[PDB]
Image 1 (cartoon, rainbow, N blue to C red):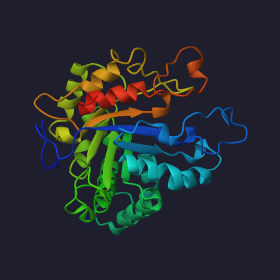
Image 2: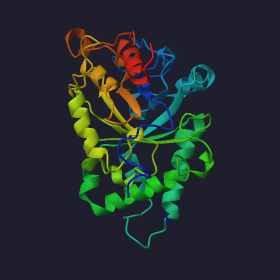
Image 3: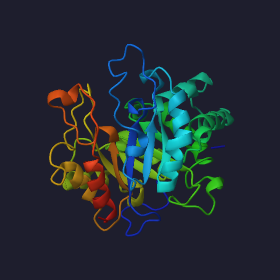
Length: 325
């Protein structure tokens, strides 16, 4: 048998100090094997260990359809990348899309109504944990929920709640395996939720009690007042220590147009987000999408070429988030 979090609102203190969270596109890693006809079969400049040593947590965004094979990538990760990141103290988690989870719910024949066998949700959670987290000794799972249909349909809300509860038995504050451990401790297994910057569309009330962090996709904000507005939308469901606001770096052939992390670093809206704090509280930290595109724009050859990065935005966000130099 599987409301809001235990504490909500602005919290003057947090169990873990504010962190910088980084999304890493595995199909842009040097060790990955892209398709034969791919225009970027070469020109791959960045490796995973190139990220700054002060990154607290990195999330591997692995998409099998974006490359031909990942065997070399995982061999390099197990041999080279992961020991170095562990030496630096950087946690590594794995991002999974909610669409894949709903597909797995559907394969089991679940509609999500009462009288169903909730052990099937536990089966799905264990399979996902073994494949995505345990297989490569990762530190937890990040569920990306950017589906507008979840909020509209009761059965989808039920399904999401049940799969996140089944996951809470394996990761997060509710997991018995994390007994006496806290985010930031060695061996802690994280349960992370990234979603809309709209709390209602996010359906964060279904996961607030089981997740360590809530990552709001504030990719179009860039103003402290707008982030305050988003946070006031979330504050009655989660506490500020769970909340992370973020920005997105321009991607090649993206069509999305996220403008907060372009131009001068110190005056960018991305650094306003990194510097932002909840009034009367401390935040969970700051996150950035596509670390390999740090500093890139949508202009000129940037839209169509891959380039190395100096991680200037990443370093400055770390400084503003953690209050260090």
